[PDB]
Image (cartoon, rainbow, N blue to C red):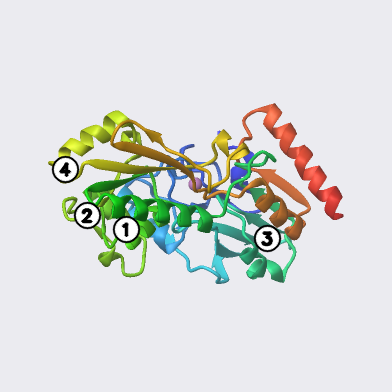
């Protein structure tokens, strides 16, 4: 059954609650972003209103074939009414189209649901600064202090210099980048840009990217593999066996593959700096795993919650075990005591 942390009290709303059939008493289903765990259950046969951003909107229409009449896109940073309730969608700094939602309840309670987010100081100067938030439905993906990672800027600098260097030394080297969902486009686009190439991908993935309202996107991507030296593949295929195979496919146009696996966190973040990262090499094929996160680090999360000073916090990630739940509650109590709310 639909769990409690997907329900918004004193409304008939749910958030990311599409895999439970008809939820008893839901008049409107919100979708925070186009990732499968979140949209799981949607299809062309869904006949209740869905509320979402314009971009998530384009992907439901064209990737899932949901009927236009049921998609309700809303602009960001704008006070809107949905079944008698004031709401606002805010940028989540997760993947394209990803939003946080503010609900203003009839009784005067204010509720922020973060969806998936990477907390940032820029959020402290949004519509959030203008009033008090009583309840916080929080992406707690990395709520533990071991979870440090570099900024997105630093990681992009690394990958750019790595790729430029390798291709200037050996002009017959191919760059390959792994992907399995939206998000993390900056990796492959920034590499393509330093290298004077467009990115080449499958038809399904080109379609996916054509939905994202990216500026000058027609100039940055293609379905013509051959005319491009930055290729996207299924993340599954990023390994020595799957790369060697793909190397054959290019027909002696390239002798070396340099490839990037944008991970979330990996235990090597507990020891090594971004400057000191190294690849796995098997002959003419190297694989870098780079820690490009679209979720808050522990410290970014902590700062945002201590700035927001909510009265109650409800987790949406790592909720399935008592050990996780108990650990999170401990950190929430530390933050509240250190900051005095
Ligand atoms: Ni997500």
From the image, tell me which residue sits under label 4: 250
Q: Quadrant of the N terminus?
A: top right
Badge 1: how crowded within 10 Å, few (<14), some, or many (20+)?
A: many
Q: Is residue 9 visible?
A: no
Q: Secondary structure at mark 1?
A: helix
User: Which label is found at residue 192?
Assistant: 1
Answer left or right for 53 relative to 164.
right
Q: How far apart, in angstroms, are the residues tagged by discs 4 and 2?
A: 11 Å
Determine contact: label 4, label 2, CB under 8 Å: no
From the image, tell me which residue sits under label 2: 228
Which residue is pictured at 70% across the width and 28% down the height? 323
> Dividing the picture into quarters, in which one does residue 249 lie?
top left
Which residue is pictured at 57% across the width and 45% down the height? 273
Q: Is residue 96 above or below residue 215?
A: above
Q: How far apart, in angstroms, are the residues tagged by discs 2 and 3?
A: 52 Å
Label 1 within 8 A of ligand 1 by Cβ: no
Residue 140: x, y in percent? 63, 43
Badge 4: how crowded within 10 Å, few (<14), some, or many (20+)?
A: few
Q: Secondary structure at mark 3?
A: loop
Q: For the image shown, how many numbered marks are present on the structure? A: 4
Query: Which comes before the other along the chain, label 2 or label 1?
Result: 1
User: Which label is found at residue 105?
Assistant: 3
Q: How far apart, in angstroms, are the residues tagged by discs 2 and 1?
A: 9 Å
* Camera-side residue of 146 and 314: 146
């Amino acid at each position: 059954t639909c769990p409690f942390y997907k329900k918004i009290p004193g409304t008939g709303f749910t958030v990311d609650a599409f895999q439970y059939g008809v939820v008893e008493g839901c008049t409107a289903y919100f979708l925070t972003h186009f990732h499968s765990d979140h949209y799981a259950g949607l299809s062309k046969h869904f006949t209740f209103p869905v509320y979402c951003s314009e971009i998530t909107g384009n992907l439901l229409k064209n990737k899932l074939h949901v009927q236009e009449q049921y998609i309700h896109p809303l602009p960001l940073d704008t006070e809107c009414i949905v079944n008698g309730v004031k709401v606002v969608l805010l940028d989540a700094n997760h993947c394209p189209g990803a939003v946080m939602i503010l609900f203003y309840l009839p009784n005067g309670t204010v509720i922020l649901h973060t969806g998936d987010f990477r907390a940032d100081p820029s959020m402290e100067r949004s519509l959030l600064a203008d009033q008090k938030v009583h309840m916080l439905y929080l992406d707690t993906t990395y709520c533990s202090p071991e979870y440090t990672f570099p900024s997105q800027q630093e990681v992009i600098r690394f990958a750019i210099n790595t790729a430029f260097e390798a291709v200037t030394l050996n002009p017959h080297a191919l760059v390959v980048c792994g992907t399995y969902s939206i998000g993390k486009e900056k990796v492959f686009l920034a590499i393509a840009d330093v290298l004077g190439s467009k990115v080449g991908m499958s038809q399904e993935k080109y379609k996916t990217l054509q939905c994202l309202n990216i500026p000058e996107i027609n100039s940055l991507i293609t379905t013509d593999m051959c005319s491009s030296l930055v290729h996207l593949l299924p993340m599954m295929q990023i390994n020595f066996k799957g790369l060697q195979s793909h190397l054959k496919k290019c027909g002696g146009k390239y002798n070396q593959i340099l490839a990037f696996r944008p991970t979330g966190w990996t235990h090597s973040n507990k020891f090594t700096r971004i400057a000191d990262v190294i690849p796995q090499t098997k002959g003419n094929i190297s694989i870098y795993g780079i820690p490009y996160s679209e979720h808050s680090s522990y410290l970014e999360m902590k700062r945002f919650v201590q700035w927001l000073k909510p009265q109650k916090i409800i987790p949406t990630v790592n909720v399935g075990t008592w050990k996780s739940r108990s650990t999170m509650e401990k950190y929430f109590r530390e933050w509240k005591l250190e900051a005095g709310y």
